Amino acid sequence: FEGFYKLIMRRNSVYVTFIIAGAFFGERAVDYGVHKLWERNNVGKRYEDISVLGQRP
Amino acid sequence: IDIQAAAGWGIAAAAGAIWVVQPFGWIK
Amino acid sequence: IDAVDASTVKRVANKYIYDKDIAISAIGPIQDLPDYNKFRRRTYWNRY
């Protein structure tokens, strides 16, 4: 808590590391959330939802 | 202030390398 | 006084100086004096 907190606002190297970590996780969290809502809005329309998938003849 | 700052930026650079290049699977 | 060593000065300076607000009182031909944001920014060093 206080240890990381105090380091972030007192050393710019820790703050830059904090920015990189927040960019990395915040980007993945949004990409995960966007894709979950894309899946909920497109039920039945995915390539893996084709009934005849695998029997061409 | 000279070694602490050097380790701090070395950590920032290493995290940035892991962030730009994301070799999640090269940990072998 | 003797108790105030180099570690003491840095500790006290971080409590009173680092990234702290300042008060400015200027008079005369002071157009070239930097503004509040310039003085405010110069209370920390971003290379550390």
Image (cartoon, coloured by chain):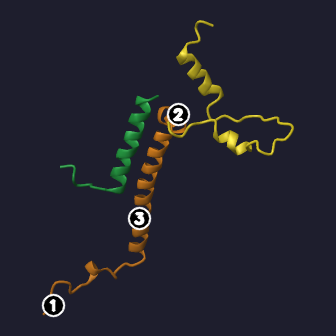
Task: Name the quadrant containing residue C5.
Answer: top right
For this view, does A11 lie left or right of residue B16? Answer: right
Residue A31's disc is 3
User: Which sits in the foreground, C2 or A22?
Assistant: C2
Whole-percent x and y of residue C23?
A: 77, 34
Residue at the spot 27% in from the left edge and 54% down from the top edge: B24
Q: Which chain does tag 3 point to?
A: A
Helix, strand or loop at label 2? It is helix
Task: Give how far across and how far down residue B8 sits, in percent.
Answer: 41, 37
Residue on which the image places disc 1: A56
Where is A25 relative to A50, above or below?
above
Nearer to us: label 3 or label 2: 2
Please state the horizontal and vertical placement of residue B21, each as a whole percent of the image.
32, 56
| Left or right of B17 on screen, residue C42 | right
Residue under circle 2?
A6
Q: Which chain is yellow?
A: C
Q: Residue at x 40, y 43 (%)?
A: B12
Distance between the alpha carbons at the discs numbered 3 and 2: 30 Å
Tell me the distance, in whole angstroms, between the alpha carbons under discs 3 and 1: 34 Å
Rendered residue at 39%/79% (across/down) = A42
Q: Amino acid at mark 1?
A: Arg
First of labels 3, 1 by sequence position = 3
Mark 2 residue crowding within 10 angstroms, few (<14) / some (14–19) / many (20+): few
| Residue C43 location (% of width, % of height) | 63, 35
Asked if the residue under mark 1 is in contact with the one under mark 2, i.e. CB atoms within 8 Å, the reply is: no
Tell me if mark 3 has few (under 14), some (14-19) or many (20+) residues whose alpha carbon lies within 10 angstroms of its own.
few
Instruction: Name the colour assigned to chain A in the rendering.
Output: orange
Closest to the observer, C9 or A32: C9
Q: Nearer the viewer, mark 2 or mark 1?
A: 2
Q: Colour of chain B?
A: green
Type of amino acid at the residue the image marks with label 2: Lys
State the count of labels: 3
